[PDB]
Length: 330
Image 1 (cartoon, rainbow, N blue to C red):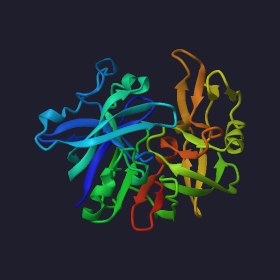
Image 2 (image 1 turned 135 degrees about the vertical axis):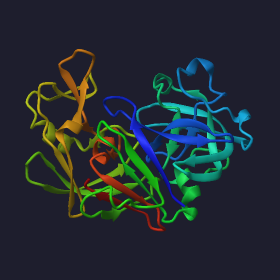
Image 3 (image 1 turned 180 degrees about the vertical axis):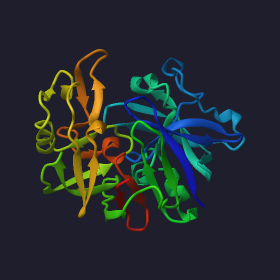
């Protein structure tokens, strides 16, 4: 089997991407944030604290003839930006782009943090990291991909995120028309439950390539590119007026600047992030100070190849017995 679904930026900055997901019988369609950095599929629901719901579409298990309470199961998750959610669990039929999993754990939110309440466009998250990170207790649950894997034509999914435009998540096949050149594959460590890999280096603009190992995660659920302070400083040093602002919470730059590209290495291959991808616009409405899309990972504890990086590539998440990651230009 295979599945194919369009993923759409939630706003003009590509702060996140939402993909329609069918849950239950009859189908209830919710727009979920596919997150290769976590492993829980959770939704706004009829059980979510009313004051914490603000425009989202909710899942109502009682209206689904295939929903079953997973008795005794609870979940609770916190993300790298400090947001969180928690609740109980149902199993139900979940379909993405034509690919159907029966008995998928659908984690129903009883509580969500303010950042989720404020994102009216995000009805929940669909985790695509390794199932070892799933937070359901006392019986850990599998991701949608993990449940689908054996039925897929090939045990893979691909992320093809657009810049200021829709893109595609495919399950079970590689669309050879969706990228240019070849896909370069690179080793993955699953030891921390992430799609963790080591980039071979970077370049800033037309600068020479610096060969250096950068361990980080491929995370569709993180907006920006978080890299070591040395790398990030080298990038922003090429932008007149750019500075790290503790009050704003990262590097800012004059909105009048033309940003240089940033290249990252995948083995001997190179992915180029155009400068425009690194512009996250005014820090506040009307400001001439703009927020940068490359930020330091110091104090996160891990480097994160988020959407800024991933949207510059066609990315293969290969869930074979020994997982790997593939990157192609597009």
